[PDB]
Amino acid sequence: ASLDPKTGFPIKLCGGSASAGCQPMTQAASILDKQRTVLAGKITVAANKVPVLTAAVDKMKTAKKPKLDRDYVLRYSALYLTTLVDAMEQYCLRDANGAKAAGGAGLPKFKETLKPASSSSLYSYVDTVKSGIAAVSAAAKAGDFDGVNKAAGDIKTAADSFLSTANPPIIFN
Ligand code: CLA
Image (cartoon, rainbow, N blue to C red):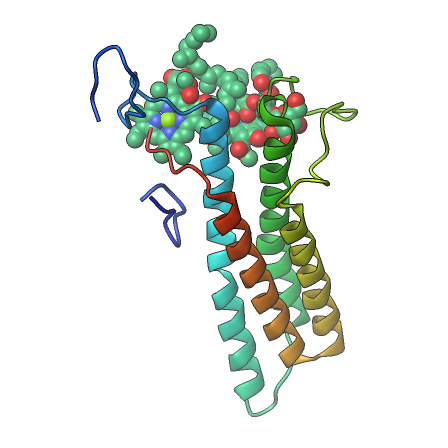
C-alpha cells in the first residue's frame, strides 16, 4: 500500500477474471505500472535519505570549530539528488507518453521521438528538486550550514508532494 522507507520495496483469487489479483498469473498490472512502482520506490529511498544529510549538517554546526564538508554535501548530492531527480524525470516521462517510455519505442537512445518529461502535470515538483540541488551546492561552496538544511527540506517536501499527486500503484508481483 506504500513503499518501504529504506529498502523501497512494496510493503484476491478469481477464475476467468484478473480481479487485480496480487498473485502472479492473475496480476492485472501493466509492465508500465511495475516500472512506475520501481521508480517510485527509488524516489522513496532517496527522499528518506534527506533526513540523514540534515543530521550530518547539524553535527557539523554544533562542533567546536564548525566547518561545512563541501565533499560530504557534494557527494550526498551526487549520490542521492541525482538519483531522485532522474527517477522523478522518468516517472514524469512514463506519465506523459504512456507505453512509449516503457520500452515501446525501443532501447533508450538519443532522438527518442517521444513526449518529453517536461510539460508533465507532475514536472513542477521535479523543478523544485533541481532548485534544491543548486541550493545544496551553492550553500556548500558558501559555507552556509542553514542553507544546506533548508534546501534539503525543500527537496524533501517536493518529493513527498510528487508521490502524493502521483498515487503510484504499489504492485506486489
Ligand atoms: C536480467 C537482467 C536485468 C534485470 C533483472 C533488470 C531489472 C530492471 N531493469 Mg534493467 N536492463 C538490463 C538488465 C536487467 N534489468 C539490461 C541488460 C538493459 C539494457 C538493455 C537494461 C535497461 C533498462 C532500462 C533502460 C530500464 C531498466 C529498468 C529495470 C527495472 C524494471 C524491469 C523492466 O523494465 O522490465 C521491462 C521488461 C521488458 C520491457 C521486456 C523484457 C522481457 C520480460 C522481462 C520477460 C517477459 C516474459 C514473458 C512472461 C514471456 C513471453 C510472453 C510473450 C507474450 C512474449 C528493473 C529494476 C527500468 C527502470 O525502471 O529502471 C530505472 C528502465 O527504465 N533496465
